[PDB]
Amino acid sequence: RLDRYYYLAKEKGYRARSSFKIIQINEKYGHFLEKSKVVIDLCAAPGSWCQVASKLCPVNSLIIGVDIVPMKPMPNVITFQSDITTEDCRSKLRGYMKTWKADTVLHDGAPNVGLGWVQDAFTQSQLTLQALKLAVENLVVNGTFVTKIFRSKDYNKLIWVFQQLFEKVEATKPPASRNVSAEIFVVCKGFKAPKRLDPRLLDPKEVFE
Ligand SMILES: C[S@@+](CC[C@H](N)C(=O)[O-])C[C@H]1O[C@@H](n2cnc3c(N)ncnc32)[C@H](O)[C@@H]1O
């Protein structure tokens, strides 16, 4: 909570304790950030995962962060304000991406407005599906997708959809997540980059019953 990771992150200049979650996931799952010349960070504010990517990615990497709340600028990182569930976000990201494909798409989204446990879990699951849809549109073949996901009655359905689009799909809970009961992280590796993509594979009405 206000624990060891909170204060280490402060002292190192990271904007949030959650910096350690992606550092630890990256260290266990093959240092994908060090291999990523283009990174999209979804639901990024205040921006500590963007800071991690800025530190670990090759120099001259393209790092793009998006959140509903404004983020303070970071050197050599692009940030903008949008709702990742919207066409607005879909269009702004495409302008920054130009002809590039992303090596890695990160997602650490969670609802801001509390609506009770059941609906907060569903909002988070909807966020995760939208983040996945953006990753499917932007990832290079064999790219990586890392997402926070809440434990809920829709977790299994999201995992299944992930397994249709990635060679390897693994749940993880790094040390900096140990005492955060709601959350698991899913590392998706080897984006299949299908020529034929099913609209239903990413349709919320089909995924969520
Ligand atoms: C857990 S924080 C992300 C922390 C970030 N990984 C870091 O290290 O600084 C979750 C963020 O998701 C954002 N969020 C929730 N729903 C969103 C949406 N629909 N579109 C964009 N951002 C959203 C919230 O504004 C919040 O900033």
Image (spheres, helix red, strand yellow):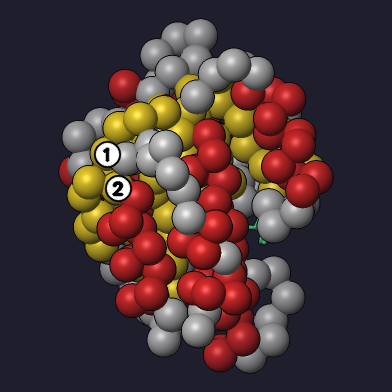
Whether tag 1 and tag 2 are in contact, CB under 8 A, the answer is: yes
Residue 134, image x, y percentages: 57, 45
Q: Amino acid at mark 2?
A: Phe
Q: Secondary structure at mark 2?
A: strand
| Mark with earlier residue (1, 2) | 2
Asked where in the image residue 141 lies, by quadrant, the reply is: top left
Residue at far top of view: 60
Residue at far front of view: 196
Q: Is residue 70 visible?
A: no
Of the pair 142 and 44, the residue shown nearer to us:
142
The residue that mark 1 highlights is 190
Q: In the displayed structure, would residue 137 be above or below residue 17? A: above
Q: Residue at x 54, y 39 (%)?
A: 137
Q: Residue at x 53, y 34 (%)?
A: 138
Q: Residue at x 25, y 55 (%)?
A: 169
Residue 20, image x, y percentages: 37, 47
The residue that mark 2 highlights is 166
Ligand 1 picture quarter: bottom right
Looking at the image, residue 149 sits to the left or right of residue 14; the answer is left
Of the pair 131 and 163, the residue shown nearer to us:
163
